Image (spheres, rainbow, N blue to C red):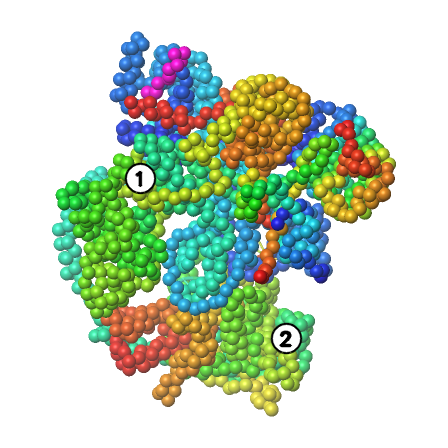
Amino acid sequence: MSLLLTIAKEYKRLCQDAKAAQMMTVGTVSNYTTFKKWTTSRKEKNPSLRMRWAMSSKFPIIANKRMLEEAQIPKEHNNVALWEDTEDVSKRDHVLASASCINYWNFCGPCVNNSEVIKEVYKSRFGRLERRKEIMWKELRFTLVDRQRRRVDTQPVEQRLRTGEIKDLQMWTLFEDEAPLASKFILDNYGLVKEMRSKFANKPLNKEVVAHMLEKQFNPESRFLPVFGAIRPERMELIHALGGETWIQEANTAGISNVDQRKNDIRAVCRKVCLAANASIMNAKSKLVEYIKSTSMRIGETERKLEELILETDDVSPEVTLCKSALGGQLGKTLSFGPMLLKKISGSGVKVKDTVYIQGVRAVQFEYWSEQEEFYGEYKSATALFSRKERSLEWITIGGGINEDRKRLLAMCMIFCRDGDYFKDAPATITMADLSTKLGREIPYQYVMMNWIQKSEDNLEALLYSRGIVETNPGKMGSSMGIDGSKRAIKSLRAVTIQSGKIDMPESKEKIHLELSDNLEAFDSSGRIVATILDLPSDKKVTFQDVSFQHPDLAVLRDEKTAITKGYEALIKRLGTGDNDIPSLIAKKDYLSLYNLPEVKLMAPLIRPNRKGVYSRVARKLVSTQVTTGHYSLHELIKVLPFTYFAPKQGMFEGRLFFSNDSFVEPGVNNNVFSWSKADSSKIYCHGIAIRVPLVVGDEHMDTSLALLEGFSVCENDPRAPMVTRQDLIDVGFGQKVRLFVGQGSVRTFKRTASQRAASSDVNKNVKKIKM
Amino acid sequence: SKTFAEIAEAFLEPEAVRIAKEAVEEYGDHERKIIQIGIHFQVCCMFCDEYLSTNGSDRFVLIEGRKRGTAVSLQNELCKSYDLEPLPFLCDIFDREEKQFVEIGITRKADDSYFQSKFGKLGNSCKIFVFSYDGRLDKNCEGPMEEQKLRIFSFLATAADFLRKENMFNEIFLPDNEETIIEMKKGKTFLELRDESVPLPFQTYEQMKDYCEKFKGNPRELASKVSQMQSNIKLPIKHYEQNKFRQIRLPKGPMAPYTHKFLMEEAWMFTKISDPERSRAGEILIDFFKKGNLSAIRPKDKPLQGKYPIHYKNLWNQIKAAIADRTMVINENDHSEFLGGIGRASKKIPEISLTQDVITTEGLKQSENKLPEPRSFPRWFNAEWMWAIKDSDLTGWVPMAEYPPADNELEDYAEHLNKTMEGVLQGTNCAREMGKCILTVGALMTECRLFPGKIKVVPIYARSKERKSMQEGLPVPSEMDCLFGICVKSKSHLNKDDGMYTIITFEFSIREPNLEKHQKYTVFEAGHTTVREVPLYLYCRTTALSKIKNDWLSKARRCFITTMDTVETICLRESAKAEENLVEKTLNEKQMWIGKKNGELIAQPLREALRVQLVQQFYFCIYNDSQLEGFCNEQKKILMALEGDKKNKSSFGFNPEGLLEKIEECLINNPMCLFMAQRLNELVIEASKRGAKFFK
Amino acid sequence: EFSIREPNLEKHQKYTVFEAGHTTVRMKKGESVIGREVPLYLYCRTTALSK
Amino acid sequence: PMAPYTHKFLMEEAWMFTKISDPERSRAGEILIDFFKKGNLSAIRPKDKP
Amino acid sequence: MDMKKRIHLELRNRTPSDVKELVLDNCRSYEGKIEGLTDEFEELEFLSTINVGLASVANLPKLNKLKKLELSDNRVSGGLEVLAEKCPNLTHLNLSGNKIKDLGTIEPLKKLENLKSLDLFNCEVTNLNDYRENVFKLLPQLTYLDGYDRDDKEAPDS
RNA sequence: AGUAGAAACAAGGGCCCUG
């Protein structure tokens, strides 16, 4: 308004100068950032000192002037000063004041209507508080603690994201007029944005603060700390008040934040799909990638794509590793040999060949590494630090707390190093059948011995005996391990050391881009294997909740419901741009041409034939009523259209619309067959399966340009087309051109015609056509 | 991040990433070019778009991703089969419905330069299409399919936004054909220097580069030089057991006198009851003035010791007068001017206005810094240490905040222990000195901030609370305001930190002085005071302060923190070894050595030894200087050697004599260092009865 | 327990309450039945018992 | 303060979903599963803040 | 969205003086307060405002020719006295889904002598004893209630 | 006078201002 005119006058006055003109004319807008630093630069060494030296003054604070006049803030209220008319040297539009004035404001100052929005701004900290309040403390005890150091997360966070995904989210929730082009993360996560926007809209707020708080709300604070007991963010946030080196405040904190359930579900899904793809013999890679992209899952309220969550988590499991490898997702330098965990500290080496005789004479190649190396190892409640040297376990130290775990870790370590005579001459019990190739897929002797150990405890005992046994020398009695896993004995194993106190887990902020084979075995720029499918449980049955296996092979439904779902899918795919589609027809109010679509003609056979006319009448009725005016809900037409193909008739409509398979849908209420919500207006749930509706048109519910962006695209710039805003963008015609401003310092030309194709296939196919 | 490939993987398909990687490896070019190529390749892909001809066959056939030789082979194969002319250069894609190759280009500059160069190079042989990240197109034929254009412009827009966000949208990562050679613009002067900073045997950076890039390891010469250097050194190694530590040699001379600004043991104070209304200093100093004792004082012109007594006397009279005027202000006279160092600041003399003749008149040699002089061991320190351990007839000397609520046993334990310690400590004498320093320094700092360029009057006081007897008698004991003396500042124009603003101290005592200890003071005989009647003395001196000292002295509550840390650590460590609450027992039973008496050792429970550590910390806060810093930094070696002796660890060293020298170097005219050094000598002596590595 | 009636603070003190989406109500309409959507509440409470 | 509700269940403020009774599934474990099949319970998703 | 944009959109260049009906359902109004309405709307005879987070009708401007209103899905409580002054020629009203605690709030509506039908569903008042009869005795001018007249006479379509 | 250290202060800018 008048303010706008004032800004224009100021811009004019400023351009009248020469230097300001040169700087606002040369270069791009990014220079602004630079200019933001050369100004207002001043620091202090000991702010505490200067704060005590300043607050001892009369007016140590600055403040706005007009805000005080408008607020009617007086001076010398009760013989105590609050401020005096002056001009600070830096701002030139601020006036000195005292701290007392702040109290005045807080006590007899202007009041806003409501302020509960704060609870949303700082939700993380109110969540901390609530989690605290729901705790049941317990007694206090004194004792020594085995505090292990390690990297963990201290901030419970749902839908952990990256930074590039967060920067756009802030802009799309607060500054939409200044928004950039729509990124994929937005189009995919629409309901999330809608939620975050519903709260911070039509409110008096400082927005920078909100953006900072959102960054904190989406950041898991990772720290390298000493830790004891279970590992959960709910605890690490207050670990300081649970136990130290000498004391422990017992307390139960198991039933809060429901975090690890999500991770175990994810890992179960990964295992399932990995096994599925393994069922193949030549395309398990593409099979797995398809199973991935053909799957989704729910998180709290929202539905997220699997491949998106997998690239955000940090669960170092032999399942997640494979997936993140298929999708080209980088990851850390962490190994996995069966159930155990490993991490290399130092050393090097290279592969080498050797053979062993299984029964009598049966040569079988097995490899090892020819050098000295050092490794950390972590099994359940047990730690170890060992070294391998030319097919031998040189030394090892342990700091666990259990005998069974100790023995299992030791055995898996001996195997990992091919130490012992068994690798020189395998036992009679094993045979060529147990060797490998369940159905052709070979197996190195390593995992062979692994399963041979997991089979019987006596194999494990014999393996331990394979390690040298001697008499426990004096003094070392405490640092010794028997066959049962006892901290001391009269005769103990060879080259072993025990101690109380776990080992400090190493650390490295490194990333690596690895690959894998057609047999699901990943490699890392070397002959080393980081993961496989033999190191995970064999198999198990589980009933996954809130999941979508929209893939034929990964499906249990029959042809009937599947046919219905595919008909609905095709009918939605006709929700795109271009004439002959339903949006253009609605705009033209051609409610009749919809009845003659081919998709309804393909779904018609599924309708109950003895009452198809009556239902048809009702459907057509609703459609006309919605179309003639303009007040429609897109989620109801897509539901009732399949019935409008036939001819109307007369009869009593009970209220339900049945198909030929005793499955119905009701017009207005959600049911198992067709459900949706105003929260997430970009999804349609049929038989549990989810369907993503494109964003081409927006009904009464959708209340922004976000619902139109999948209908637009970029095109060659045309200076003839007009320049408009983001709100009039809805009044254009399908196939038209228009210029527009995007983000900052950028103008382009758009056309309301979509392109459903992506780059994945158009690249993969064209590539495979080159390897011939 | 961490590599251009990972970056490209952000908005590209890893397939094209690997493709462009293998390509650059083939041509062995800088791997910063992974991006451009991938983009071109992906464009070609999204061009083909699974389009089909009338015969149901593929229309476009890729040539870019393939090898160069294979690509040329296929190009010639097609030029032959379809009977086309072979092109001189290679292309990217070929179509069948038209039977003419097609070349794709891309650029950022909004100009035709790239398309003009390409069209000159190839004329009109084949179809060329160059897109721009900002929505432009230049070609030599009809436009492509619509969908192709849309999908290409959209992809390019996203990529350009990403790059601009990563600051990589420059010629470096997106160069044209020509600007493909980036290099540091090595000038002339820089080279002239680089060829001049080379080590001796070489004389040009080229020789050094050739020697380093090809350097090979010759372990034998290395080991030989190692041994040679190992023979011409003869590094001494000295196991302490054989080579013991002598005692420390303290300096010799007079005794180290009192240095702290305020008196602690010899201080006498007048007390009154505190009213919440009158709580400021300028008020209490008058309240105490009305009853007449502060005015009853009337010193005489004959001092027991000191100098310039007339100035002090006149200043005291002026102080009384100002107090009577209800204005804590003083006028600038000759006396105050002399005591406040008003005009005794040097006068400046520029050299431009100086000649050899001016120097001869009045000698202007370089100032001969008169470093401090040594001192001897003070015999009055143990007295103060023993006096600062006993109660003071009151408590609450040091203000403290309140205790918050509690919900779990942990906070209960913490509160209990903290209450015990605070109640034990608040009753001592060191505590009243801490509170005195706190409040007086606060007042002085406020004054220096508000009333500079003006001589003021500030009291030396404190606030406390009489102890709590049983419920019998008068309950709810009252509070008390105590006054130990008077203080005065002088124009604290603290233009800069580390500055100096001279204060003056008028204190009250009932104990005659000693020349060795109370050397700087100037005592007067005032009169008598009650308790019966007793004589009165008036200790007077001069000193100064700074912002730094004022601030650190006001923050004198850290000693509590340190002491609590030590004690709680001991108690928790003793309680954990047995897995039981052993805190009260550890405080009432565990004995700690304190000192010697009659040649025997002395001990008392920790509950009473806390006071020793507290006084130690207080003195560290008081006498802190560079000397004490160096000492306390160099004494750790001795303690570690002692510990090694206790555990039969055969310690050793290279040159202990130098360590003793370094230590004894920083012992000058600072009582605390001397005291602690003598006590350390006594420690090693007493331990020699139980340990080695020490000489007598 | 399920409910379609928001609570009052006094009578409902031992109860923890939520808001669980919506539901439907059914009533006659001439010779047919209709359905009118309403909210839905969830009443949470703990208590003991004996034999 | 006023005396609050004490009984275990709700009398007047209650609510109930309905379905037809099958004598072959006349048990709690079966009735509950059947009620759950139609998916009206799964729709019950209480928000965080009460 | 927002009632302002919704309205400006519904007004496809049409003056706010020749319309006979308006709808603003599934919108939002800050502070539950009307925004964009004036006395310019004279020929308007129908209105529909549903699920807009409204809480009071104080701002509503005078509208004489209006003869039907819908305020369901909101949380209006104790603002019924204003309706008489602004819209005295009103006949049909609907409030199902709002915060109505007692019959005292509904007394002002007696002054709407032109009132014929009223709709109260899902409100607390309905959970009382002898509410339909007591209401009828309070508002004798009112004939239909929630779609049913005395003796439970189902009302016709329209 | 004094401070403290291994050099600095014991006001500084233009009759007026300031940490």
Nearer-the-camera pick, B488 or B210? B210
Q: CA distance from mark 2 to mark 1?
A: 84 Å
Q: Residue at x 58, y 46 (%)?
A: D46
- Which percent across, then down, holds residue B572? 43, 70
Q: Which mark is residue B461?
A: none
Tell me the crowding category of disc 2: few under 14, some 14 to 19, or many 20 or more residues within 10 angstroms, Cα based. Answer: many
The amino acid beneath tag 2 is Leu
Q: Residue at x 55, y 33 (%)?
A: A673
Q: Residue at x 44, y 32 (%)?
A: A551
Relative depth, front residue between E84 and B4: E84
Residue that label 1 marks:
A522
Q: Residue at x 67, y 26 (%)?
A: A652
Q: Quadrant of the C terminus of chain B?
A: bottom left
Instruction: Name the spot of residue B208 as percent of width and height, x first.
Output: 21, 42
What secondary structure characterizes most of the magenta part? Answer: loop
Q: Is residue E12 left or right of residue B575?
A: right
Q: Chain of mark 1?
A: A
Residue that carries the numbered disc 2 in the rendered image: B285
* Residue B61 located within the stretch drawn in magenta: yes
